Image 1 (cartoon, rainbow, N blue to C red):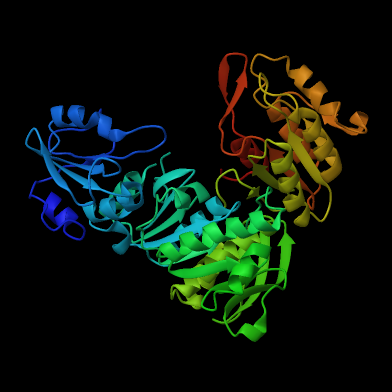
Image 2 (cartoon, one colour):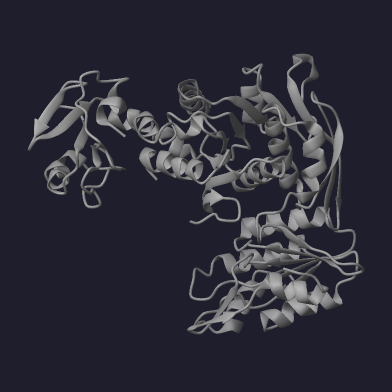
Length: 487
């Protein structure tokens, strides 16, 4: 880490200074640090140059806008201050070089879209590690090697990737947000591949608005090192982009592959949704096969097929992917299935809004030969408007609604349940059972072998809040003990 080597691609005359860390914040700047002074969200980091100098930073790189020309080298208190124009745009490349290009020292796959980013990244990291990578994730759940994921400027992204490379990671699956892409947070990253799940943007009904949105996105991907493109052809926007990208991989589970293109493709031909997951039959330009997925619902078929197409595009052999597919796991507490010989199917899911609850029930219904049970409640001392909507959704999409407690906090637990029931056409056909453990047991012990019990609202969140008390309680553990299995 040397200022002269750091800036050699952009500023040839830069003095030699040993550098420690790269920071945007004068308050945490230490002796030897490189301070980077950016103009940002109603803030000007150049205001904090004197504090950064007083903390003993070795050098400063600063926005040139209205202060200096691009590449201008100044000196303040014997500290080099180098000015760069458009420093927000260049910060990714600057940090990339500072951290020795971490995206050139592992296989980085980016995942963009409205939904399925978390699941698709976890599947990419898991499947790659089953084939012998040391894989890592960066996303909304956090950053780290698989099993060690812990809960963001262009500098933080490059630093975190460098941290993963230092820990032995050879593969990283990164959730990329629309906001991250637009604010140049991944601008200099070398993506081996870019995955598009779907675009659920309301607000885009006007042709000029859809045109400008698409124009902004096309411009961004012309500026990035996207690598191989893997696109969900079941998304209308995905299909429009596939029509313009002949080297992209088209993925479908709904017959949207156009075979006249002679491009690379992967298509589910048949799915059997059953008690413990999905049997997925598929054809592809790499060959055909059948996958035993332990994930639940149609959207998770799509997520898995995107991850498969990505790894096939990157050269992972179909035979090795097929042989490891049965080891792919759900995201913990997301449509997580619990089965046992001769027992009902139980799905634990985090769903705690009307929309998540409807999606979870629709997904669970596909796997349900008998009756669909829904065990749920609503949090106390929070917004109450969702209570009757969740009741109506449970009544509509489930055969048996079992309304119980879910963190009633200091609110009268039955008050919450009354709000849920008020949303129903026939409240009298809902079951009510208090104790959540008792309500889960009720559903699981009454359900038939070919029934599906959805236990919604907690997922992995191993507590029940009653009054001021965080009680030890887990849906996953309660269901596991009832079924005689290990959570």
